[PDB]
Length: 178
Image 1 (tube, rainbow, N blue to C red):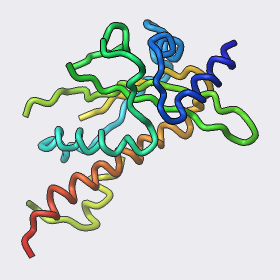
Image 2 (cartoon, rainbow, N blue to C red; image 1 turned 90 degrees about the vertical axis):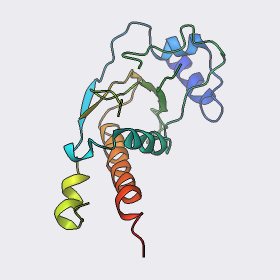
Image 3 (cartoon, helix red, strand yellow; image 1 turned 135 degrees about the vertical axis):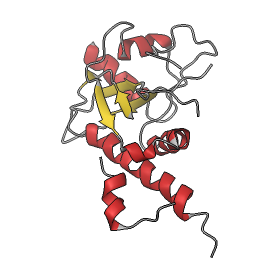
Image 4 (tube, rainbow, N blue to C red; image 1 turned 120 degrees about the vertical axis):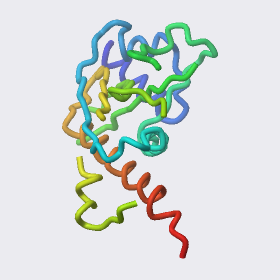
């Protein structure tokens, strides 16, 4: 019945994913500590423009993982929010079928920073991979199925390695008058 429920949830989450709080609890029990808590380290040069980077990362993650809006206009037992701060940032990822079978992965992530947000010398190869290559961003997941994290850690390593380049080019190289 676990496989049946996982397949049903995966089918429902294909396009609309108008889920139920029961489905959310099934995906992640309210109290089951995350299976894969990890930390991502960012260069210290990115300290001054943290909130812009937050917006760029929020925009860039939506490439493959979608936001949750299941069935409710109330936040009563909607999603567990470790260190929440009206505003929430949680994202669900659905695993695809692979090989001949085995797509039964649906995970919830509620990553934030180790800190909180309350507030040039040119460029080129010396700083290309010394400012974008990888202030911490702890990320934790609730793996209900077969997530197989050998293709998920990189799935957000790049997704944050590009939100850096985009932020820098929009912030530094853009306002230069021709």
